[PDB]
Length: 173
Image 1 (cartoon, rainbow, N blue to C red):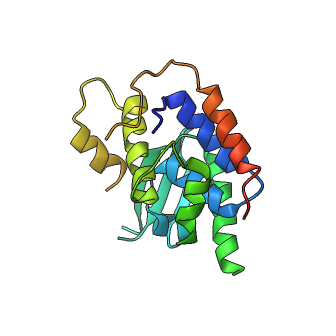
Image 2 (cartoon, helix red, strand yellow):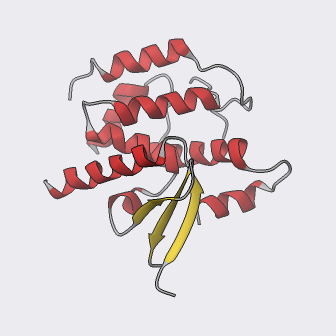
Protein backbone atom coordinates (compact mmCIF):
# COMPACT_ATOMS: atom_id res chain seq x y z
CA UNK A 1 0.00 0.00 0.00
CA UNK A 2 2.33 2.66 -1.38
CA UNK A 3 2.40 6.29 -0.24
CA UNK A 4 2.82 8.80 -3.06
CA UNK A 5 3.77 12.47 -3.21
CA UNK A 6 2.31 15.18 -5.45
CA UNK A 7 4.92 14.81 -8.19
CA UNK A 8 4.28 11.08 -8.29
CA UNK A 9 0.55 11.83 -8.40
CA UNK A 10 0.93 14.08 -11.44
CA UNK A 11 2.97 11.51 -13.38
CA UNK A 12 0.43 8.77 -12.68
CA UNK A 13 -2.26 11.05 -14.09
CA UNK A 14 -0.10 11.68 -17.17
CA UNK A 15 0.33 7.92 -17.69
CA UNK A 16 -3.41 7.25 -17.61
CA UNK A 17 -4.36 10.28 -19.70
CA UNK A 18 -1.70 9.64 -22.34
CA UNK A 19 -2.01 5.89 -22.82
CA UNK A 20 -3.50 4.47 -26.03
CA UNK A 21 -4.98 1.22 -24.77
CA UNK A 22 -8.16 1.81 -22.80
CA UNK A 23 -10.62 4.68 -22.62
CA UNK A 24 -11.61 3.29 -19.22
CA UNK A 25 -8.09 4.02 -17.98
CA UNK A 26 -8.43 7.59 -19.26
CA UNK A 27 -11.59 7.80 -17.15
CA UNK A 28 -9.68 7.09 -13.95
CA UNK A 29 -7.05 9.62 -15.01
CA UNK A 30 -9.79 12.24 -15.28
CA UNK A 31 -11.26 11.31 -11.88
CA UNK A 32 -7.83 11.67 -10.26
CA UNK A 33 -7.17 14.89 -12.10
CA UNK A 34 -10.34 16.87 -11.27
CA UNK A 35 -12.28 15.02 -8.55
CA UNK A 36 -15.68 15.24 -10.21
CA UNK A 37 -18.36 12.59 -9.78
CA UNK A 38 -18.44 10.07 -12.65
CA UNK A 39 -21.93 11.13 -13.74
CA UNK A 40 -20.74 14.75 -14.05
CA UNK A 41 -17.87 13.52 -16.20
CA UNK A 42 -20.16 11.28 -18.25
CA UNK A 43 -23.06 13.67 -18.98
CA UNK A 44 -24.97 16.89 -18.36
CA UNK A 45 -21.95 19.10 -17.66
CA UNK A 46 -19.80 21.31 -19.84
CA UNK A 47 -16.13 21.85 -19.02
CA UNK A 48 -14.11 24.95 -19.94
CA UNK A 49 -10.60 26.20 -19.34
CA UNK A 50 -10.37 28.72 -16.50
CA UNK A 51 -6.61 28.96 -15.79
CA UNK A 52 -3.34 27.31 -16.65
CA UNK A 53 -4.50 24.80 -13.99
CA UNK A 54 -8.20 25.36 -13.30
CA UNK A 55 -11.32 24.14 -15.08
CA UNK A 56 -14.82 25.66 -15.01
CA UNK A 57 -17.72 23.19 -14.89
CA UNK A 58 -21.11 24.55 -15.96
CA UNK A 59 -24.29 22.75 -15.02
CA UNK A 60 -27.83 23.15 -13.72
CA UNK A 61 -28.50 22.12 -10.12
CA UNK A 62 -29.28 33.10 -13.60
CA UNK A 63 -28.81 30.96 -16.71
CA UNK A 64 -26.30 28.48 -15.29
CA UNK A 65 -24.39 27.23 -12.25
CA UNK A 66 -20.62 27.16 -12.47
CA UNK A 67 -17.92 25.71 -10.26
CA UNK A 68 -14.21 26.34 -10.69
CA UNK A 69 -11.76 23.80 -9.31
CA UNK A 70 -8.01 23.16 -9.58
CA UNK A 71 -6.70 20.30 -11.72
CA UNK A 72 -3.64 18.08 -11.91
CA UNK A 73 -2.99 17.93 -15.67
CA UNK A 74 -3.19 20.29 -18.62
CA UNK A 75 -6.88 21.38 -18.79
CA UNK A 76 -7.01 21.03 -22.54
CA UNK A 77 -5.61 17.51 -22.21
CA UNK A 78 -8.24 16.70 -19.56
CA UNK A 79 -11.17 18.16 -21.47
CA UNK A 80 -10.14 16.34 -24.66
CA UNK A 81 -10.13 13.06 -22.70
CA UNK A 82 -13.65 13.78 -21.47
CA UNK A 83 -14.71 14.20 -25.11
CA UNK A 84 -13.29 10.79 -26.01
CA UNK A 85 -14.82 9.24 -22.89
CA UNK A 86 -18.28 10.57 -23.75
CA UNK A 87 -17.77 9.48 -27.38
CA UNK A 88 -16.95 5.88 -26.35
CA UNK A 89 -20.25 5.75 -24.47
CA UNK A 90 -22.30 7.28 -27.32
CA UNK A 91 -20.74 4.92 -29.87
CA UNK A 92 -21.77 2.02 -27.60
CA UNK A 93 -18.28 -3.78 -12.55
CA UNK A 94 -15.48 -4.60 -14.98
CA UNK A 95 -14.14 -1.11 -14.12
CA UNK A 96 -12.96 -2.31 -10.73
CA UNK A 97 -10.99 -5.32 -11.93
CA UNK A 98 -9.43 -2.92 -14.42
CA UNK A 99 -8.46 -0.71 -11.48
CA UNK A 100 -6.91 -3.73 -9.71
CA UNK A 101 -5.02 -4.91 -12.82
CA UNK A 102 -3.18 -1.60 -12.61
CA UNK A 103 -3.03 -0.73 -8.93
CA UNK A 104 -2.99 -4.02 -7.00
CA UNK A 105 -0.61 -3.73 -4.04
CA UNK A 106 -0.38 0.04 -4.53
CA UNK A 107 -3.94 1.21 -3.84
CA UNK A 108 -6.56 -1.19 -2.46
CA UNK A 109 -9.72 0.89 -1.85
CA UNK A 110 -13.13 -0.62 -1.33
CA UNK A 111 -14.45 1.92 -3.86
CA UNK A 112 -11.98 3.15 -6.48
CA UNK A 113 -14.19 6.12 -7.38
CA UNK A 114 -14.36 7.26 -3.75
CA UNK A 115 -10.60 6.73 -3.49
CA UNK A 116 -9.91 8.81 -6.60
CA UNK A 117 -12.02 11.71 -5.31
CA UNK A 118 -10.55 11.50 -1.81
CA UNK A 119 -6.95 11.59 -3.06
CA UNK A 120 -7.85 14.55 -5.29
CA UNK A 121 -9.08 16.51 -2.25
CA UNK A 122 -5.90 15.88 -0.30
CA UNK A 123 -3.62 16.92 -3.13
CA UNK A 124 -5.73 19.94 -4.12
CA UNK A 125 -5.44 21.14 -0.52
CA UNK A 126 -1.68 20.46 -0.30
CA UNK A 127 -1.11 22.15 -3.65
CA UNK A 128 -3.59 25.08 -3.70
CA UNK A 129 -5.02 25.96 -0.33
CA UNK A 130 -3.39 28.82 1.60
CA UNK A 131 -1.59 28.22 4.86
CA UNK A 132 -4.05 27.52 7.72
CA UNK A 133 -7.28 27.06 5.74
CA UNK A 134 -9.85 24.79 7.37
CA UNK A 135 -10.03 21.52 5.41
CA UNK A 136 -13.79 21.08 5.77
CA UNK A 137 -14.37 24.39 3.96
CA UNK A 138 -11.85 23.44 1.28
CA UNK A 139 -13.53 20.10 0.56
CA UNK A 140 -16.97 21.63 0.14
CA UNK A 141 -15.45 24.42 -1.95
CA UNK A 142 -13.69 22.08 -4.41
CA UNK A 143 -16.52 19.50 -4.46
CA UNK A 144 -19.97 20.76 -3.40
CA UNK A 145 -7.08 8.90 5.07
CA UNK A 146 -3.40 9.08 4.13
CA UNK A 147 -2.00 7.41 1.03
CA UNK A 148 -0.14 10.67 0.44
CA UNK A 149 3.13 12.33 1.39
CA UNK A 150 2.86 15.98 2.51
CA UNK A 151 6.03 17.20 0.82
CA UNK A 152 5.63 19.16 -2.38
CA UNK A 153 9.16 19.24 -3.80
CA UNK A 154 10.14 15.56 -3.44
CA UNK A 155 11.06 13.98 -6.78
CA UNK A 156 8.59 11.56 -8.34
CA UNK A 157 8.84 7.85 -7.48
CA UNK A 158 10.38 6.35 -10.59
CA UNK A 159 10.32 2.68 -9.60
CA UNK A 160 6.59 3.10 -8.98
CA UNK A 161 6.09 4.74 -12.36
CA UNK A 162 7.99 1.97 -14.18
CA UNK A 163 5.79 -0.60 -12.41
CA UNK A 164 2.62 1.18 -13.55
CA UNK A 165 3.91 1.86 -17.05
CA UNK A 166 4.72 -1.84 -17.46
CA UNK A 167 1.27 -2.79 -16.22
CA UNK A 168 -0.53 -0.41 -18.58
CA UNK A 169 1.18 -1.81 -21.66
CA UNK A 170 1.10 -5.50 -20.74
CA UNK A 171 -2.30 -6.20 -19.17
CA UNK A 172 -4.99 -7.96 -21.20
CA UNK A 173 -8.22 -6.03 -22.01
